[PDB]
Image (spheres, coloured by chain):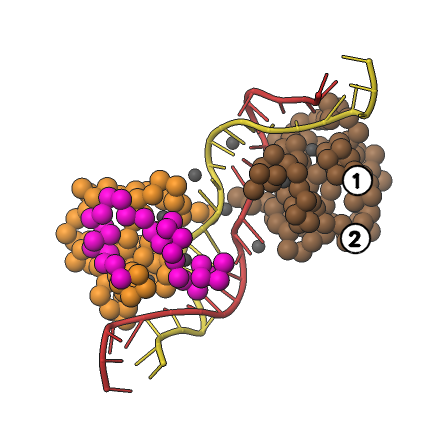
Chain colours: A orange, B brown, C red, D yellow
Amino acid sequence: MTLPHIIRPVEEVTEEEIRNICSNSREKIYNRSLGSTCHQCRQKTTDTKTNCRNPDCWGIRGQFCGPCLRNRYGEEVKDALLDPNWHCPPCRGICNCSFCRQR
Amino acid sequence: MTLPHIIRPVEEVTEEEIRNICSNSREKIYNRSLGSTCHQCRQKTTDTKTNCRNPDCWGIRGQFCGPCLRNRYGEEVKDALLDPNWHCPPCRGICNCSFCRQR
DNA sequence: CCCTGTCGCTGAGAAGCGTTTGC
DNA sequence: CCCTGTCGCTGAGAAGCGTTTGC
Ligand SMILES: [Mg+2]
Ligand SMILES: [Mg+2]
Ligand SMILES: [Mg+2]
Ligand SMILES: [Mg+2]
Ligand SMILES: [Mg+2]
Ligand SMILES: [Zn+2]
Ligand SMILES: [Zn+2]
Ligand SMILES: [Zn+2]
Ligand SMILES: [Zn+2]
Ligand SMILES: [Zn+2]
Ligand SMILES: [Zn+2]
């Protein structure tokens, strides 16, 4: 049931993705099929989300939406998309989501 | 892919299972379909194996064969089968298998 | 009134072939 | 010669709807 984690190279990042990076959490479009789930807010939406470049990462715990990465970690998804060494907060052990903060 | 853990009540234990409890690890019968995997020796065989009664347990980590439970923990599978409060060594945090001993 | 924001819950949390059997 | 025994490796290690959005 685990979704395979695929590292999208920075060269394959397209302008359409940056344009679709969410800037308002209430301006999201839900889609049970094409949407992606943000690890932080746990919403499956169609806005562009981060891609963890850590090979040891797995699943969707490396996927963060615009508002969540902006407000919970002070980082921009556009910068994370273009960063080839970017690691997700779960990989860095700094994730402050409701599940990761207790454990 | 996780096999559902089902608690078999002690009243439903049958004599055919005790007779099929393994007494020699080299006298096992491998079966990819009907066999069960012992958590300790990681062999999928048809001999009777333990059933963990802990509701919080999951998967097959509570399944131990005759020789493994006898030699690695000093307990008999027949006694474990008839014990309604029996917990697997992984549940007790005392498992000494090659994977559990390091972690 | 201002940096336009977030957690609960369920079900989830491997298994088994291969290279495997003591001093 | 005796209590008739065991580990490596791969792939595994959730996700997302619902009850969800700041002081
Ligand atoms: Mg699974
Ligand atoms: Mg569900
Ligand atoms: Mg379950
Ligand atoms: Mg395999
Ligand atoms: Mg894998
Ligand atoms: Zn989010
Ligand atoms: Zn990661
Ligand atoms: Zn987290
Ligand atoms: Zn065994
Ligand atoms: Zn157990
Ligand atoms: Zn173990």
The residue pinned by badge 2 equals B84
| Range drawn in magenta | A74-103
Tell me if mark 1 has few (under 14), some (14-19) or many (20+) residues whose alpha carbon lies within 10 angstroms of its own: some
The residue pinned by badge 1 equals B75
Q: Would residue A9 appear left or right of A92 to someone viewing this image?
A: left
Q: Amino acid at mark 1?
A: Glu
Q: Would residue B70 appear left or right of A79 to someone viewing this image?
A: right
Total marks drawn? 2
Residue A7 forms part of the magenta stretch: no
Q: Nearer the viewer, residue A52 or B35?
A: A52
Which chain contains the residue that carries disc 2? B
The residue that appears at 20% across and 53% down in the rendered structure is: A79
The image quarter containing residue D1 is top right
Q: Is residue A70 visible?
A: yes
Q: Nearer the viewer, residue A68 or B18?
A: A68
Q: Is residue B49 visible?
A: no
The residue that appears at 24% across and 56% down in the rendered structure is: A77
Whether B16 is drawn above or below A97: the answer is above
Q: Would residue A79 appear left or right of B86 to someone viewing this image?
A: left
The earlier-in-sequence mark between 2 and 1 is 1
Mark 2 or 1: the one toward you:
1
Q: Nearer the viewer, residue A63 or B102?
A: B102
